[PDB]
Amino acid sequence: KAARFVRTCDAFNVPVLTFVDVPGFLPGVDQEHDGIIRRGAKLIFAYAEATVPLITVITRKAFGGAYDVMGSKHLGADLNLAWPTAQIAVMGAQGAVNILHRRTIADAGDDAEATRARLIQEYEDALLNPYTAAERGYVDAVIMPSDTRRHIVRGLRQLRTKRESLPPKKHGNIPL
Amino acid sequence: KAARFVRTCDAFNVPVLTFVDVPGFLPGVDQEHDGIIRRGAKLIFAYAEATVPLITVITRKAFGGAYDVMGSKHLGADLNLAWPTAQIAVMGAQGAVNILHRRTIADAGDDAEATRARLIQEYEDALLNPYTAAERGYVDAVIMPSDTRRHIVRGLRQLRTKRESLPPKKHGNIPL
Amino acid sequence: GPCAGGAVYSPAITDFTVMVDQTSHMFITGPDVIKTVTGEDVGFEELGGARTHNSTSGVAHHMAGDEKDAVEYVKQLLSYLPSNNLSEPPAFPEEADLAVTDEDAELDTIVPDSANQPYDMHSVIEHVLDDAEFFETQPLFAPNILTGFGRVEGRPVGIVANQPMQFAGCLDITASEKAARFVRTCDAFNVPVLTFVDVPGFLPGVDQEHDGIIRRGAKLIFAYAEATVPLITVITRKAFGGAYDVMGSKHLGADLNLAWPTAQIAVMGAQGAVNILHRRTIADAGDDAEATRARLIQEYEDALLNPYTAAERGYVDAVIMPSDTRRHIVRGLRQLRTKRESLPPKKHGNIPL
Amino acid sequence: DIHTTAGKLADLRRRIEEATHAGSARAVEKQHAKGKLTARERIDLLLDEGSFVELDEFARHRSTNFGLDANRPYGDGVVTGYGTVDGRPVAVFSQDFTVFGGALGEVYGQKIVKVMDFALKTGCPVVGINDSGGARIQEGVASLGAYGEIFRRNTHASGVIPQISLVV
């Protein structure tokens, strides 16, 4: 749905504003079997191809591939803003601690879990925010939610003269 | 100094107005040894390459190569104006008579010099002006100094729609 | 023959100027005039003779002993270039034998042990070019850097290389301008450029600054950054500070950047670095002020004066055995010959003048 | 020695040996036990003999998160370069499962980006050999940035140069 829309806007020089709050992809055998791999890729392709102005605002969750998909700077977005409430990370804290601390947790079945829940709480307090992404410039700024309109307006003023184009080709080969 | 400036103006579509009163190049062993040949050529290159409007006004001296260098019509200047006080010639009268009349002057050591100074005075009265250049169209007009502003203004109005371009190339090979 | 007055500006604009020893002269102003105006007495030969313009003014590109050799030199020049910028230079394709020869091996020992003893970069160049043939241009001007033509697998290539034998390979105003124009010449005519690096930095001196090294040295970086022809760079030894950036670094757009095990890619010399990083650490304990610094210096050079940190970052695509330079250049040029790149549209750039 | 030129050449030969064997002997054994080949074995089957030129062989990661800086294997988990397939130019990257489970990291990603830029620049196909456990979690978002950069190249190169994915 979003992919076709983004391509439509881009083809007709309409700037795209995107707001992110996505925990990931809907789990389900059906999703895989029905082709989420090739059908989901359509959104990254649409964003990477677009040349119109792109402004992205992460209000909250931005985990794993989904973060990449939702008009991330890596795909070519021009301005990426994040609210203090944004959580930009590879994956949820629980999933992340189970991999990172699989050994230290396995140790002492005694007190297996509160230490588990402890690490989870520590992980989210250290990485479940937009500041690591801000350090690398993945987001251009962390803003007060109430300044979202000012940033959009001033960003659009500067971005309207944006000129970019993809390598010459008859056309691309977007996943079908 | 002038070369870089002319290229800057041209790159950014800024018309260049140039005023000429140059007797030639500063004599000096240092000038040659430091590379005046390749460093001086940078100005002719800048003028010949420029495609923005070019209006040149010779107020006085315009001798030898320097005349060619100062945005002459031969380099591509669009409008070349000259004041009655302009002196457009291959070289100064003295230098010119020494070559042209080397024999007639060598004759009769008696009265060597007043005849010399005579020829010089005659040469400058016949060629040290803008009229021979005006005959060949090298200058588009000889104007009253007070009409300089009118010519600049009206010339710029017609020239603003100027469209020209050099042969296709990745870039030129300006002397360095 | 003579080229006087404004006439000199025509050859100046052309790409290459070849003169003949003691039988050709170029000058904007004659001896006669500079004398009555400056009081300086100079003969035609000293003012603008072939030797003067080939080693002092930086205007001519070659001084032949006679006209016969001069004509031969231009024929050679023409043999390395295309008829126009629409095609690649002429080639007589011949597949090279990539097996390591006894000559290739020599390269593994060309770099002496002492960071000071110089070696002739000419040898390095010859070892990679077909029939070890290197057609040099401007041999007598800025000898600290070498420029010229050669062929790899029968295809013309341009060369730019620091020469450790003169001014320890340092860059300066003259070398920058000599190299800058040559690179731009090669690029305009689709000639690939191979650069060999051994530069400890820029020649220090008040004169260098006052004469405008800031804007004149910038010319070389602009040339490399602007180039779209294939670019392969080999760092044989020293590459410090900005000089490293200037000499066909990957940051400017070079396609393949190779470094020998003997390469030293760092921001600055070990001593100059430790003096800043350990200013306080050495300040404390005047007691034995120096073996400690000589230790900090030793440690700094053993830890950073090599190509490995640059390799970790991908600044150099590979650290190779010197004896394998020819192979990398040959196989690198094969892939790179189809390179297609362009700069943003513009009437022209605004290179420093 | 080391301070001598010969010593520096010997030092290189040592690093080359460590780089080509970035993964532990045990890791390689498991890979073979699963009926899978190594990253380098696969490239050798694909490219014409002797045509392979490796890029970023001595690359190493820059992370210090979760003690990751304790191990910085050469190549950082993916073998990249160019060569020929039936005499025609081809760019290639081969993910190494024996190194960090092949989890995609920052430098790991930059190496693939270099291979892709190279293929787009010279106009040759890109063959990607995939075998990775996923994102190198220790690197947090840096891992996602690498993915994004790759995705963009995939899209821009789409229909420009052939792109084939070998998932093994």
Image (spheres, coloured by chain):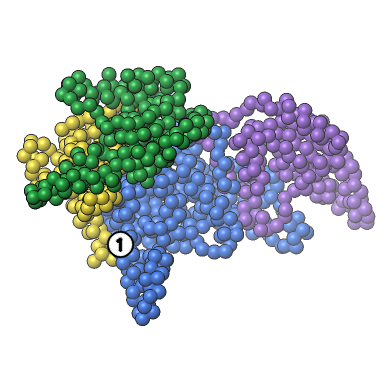
Chain colours: A green, B purple, C blue, D yellow
Residue C304, image quadrant: bottom left
Residue A91 percent across, percent down from the top left: 24, 38
User: Residue flagged by tag 1: what amino acid is it?
Assistant: Ala
Left or right of B118 in this view: C146: left
Residue depicted at x 11% and y 45%: D27
Q: Position of residue A44 (x, y in %)?
A: 32, 27
Tell me the residue at 62%/49% (across/down).
B39
Q: Which residue position is annotated with label 1? A: C303
Q: Position of residue B59 (x, y in %)?
A: 81, 41
The answer to which of A88 and D122 lies nearer the viewer is A88
Q: Is residue C79 visible?
A: no
Q: Residues within 10 Å of mark 1 (few under 14, many from 20)?
A: few
Residue C302: quarter of image: bottom left
> Can the viewer see residue A10?
yes
Residue C161 vs B58, above or below: the answer is: below
Report x, y in % for residue D104.
24, 40
In the rendered view, tell whether residue B152 sits above or below residue C241: above
Q: Is B29 positioned to the left or the right of C328 in the image?
A: right
In this view, the residue in front, C189 or A124, is A124
State the residue lying farthest toward the left: D33
Judge left or right: residue B67 versus residue C265: right
Residue shown at 17% from the left, 21% from the top: A30
Q: C290 or C302: nearer the eye?
A: C290
